[PDB]
Image: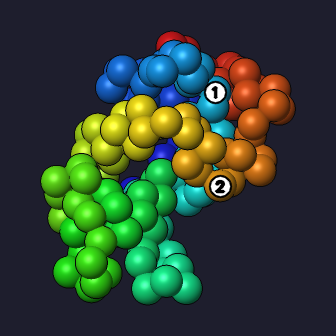
Amino acid sequence: KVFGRCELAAAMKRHGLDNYRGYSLGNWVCAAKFESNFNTQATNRNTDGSTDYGILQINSRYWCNDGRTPGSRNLCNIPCSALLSSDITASVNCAKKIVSDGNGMNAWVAWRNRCKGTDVQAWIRGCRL
């Protein structure tokens, strides 16, 4: 499913992401925009053989099981495919773990390079939240 900006903003909030670990909702929507263009089915293969899945492009090296990333962890305790669903619950659950990992949102390279320090409030303007 391809989310609309405000639709996703509302789905995210509803799931406890606004100010989760001090990150306002604008940061989460900005991250999803640049990571997958709001497409839950996005996938991208990395050079190390790991793959990034879903709306937040969660990596198979540490967070999910795809059965094809030799000696990787499954910290979120889910099959990576669960991250591609129309329902964003697993993606958000896993994201909460990642963001709590120590590096905050710096864990997402597009956030770091495209959202960090920009007017993220722009991503939620005009939405009914």
Name the residue at 49% across, 36% down: 102
- Would you say 57 lies left or right of 96 here? right
Residue receiving disc 1? 26
Q: Which residue is more in the foreground, 100 or 116?
A: 100
Name the residue at 47% across, 59% down: 57
Please tell me which of labels 2 and 1 falls first in the chain: 1
- Would you say 128 lies left or right of 100 here? right
Return the mark for residue 123: none
SS type, badge 1 = helix
**Where in the figure is residue 50, as x and y percent of width and height?**
41, 78
**Splitting the image into 4 quarters, where does residue 94 fall?**
top left
**Where in the figure is residue 109, as x and y percent of width and height?**
65, 55
The chosen color scheme is rainbow
**Where in the figure is residue 36, as x and y percent of width and height?**
55, 59
Q: Crowding at label 2, few (<14), some or many (≥20) Cα neighbours within 10 Å?
A: some
SS type, badge 2 = helix
| Amino acid on which disc 1 is placed | Gly
Residue 41 appears in the figure: no
Residue 15 appears in the figure: yes
Q: How far apart are marks 2 and 1 (CA)?
A: 16 Å
| Amino acid on which disc 2 is placed | Val
Is 100 situated above or below 106?
above
The residue furthest right is 118
Name the residue at 27% across, 78% down: 71
* Image quadrant containing the N terminus: bottom left
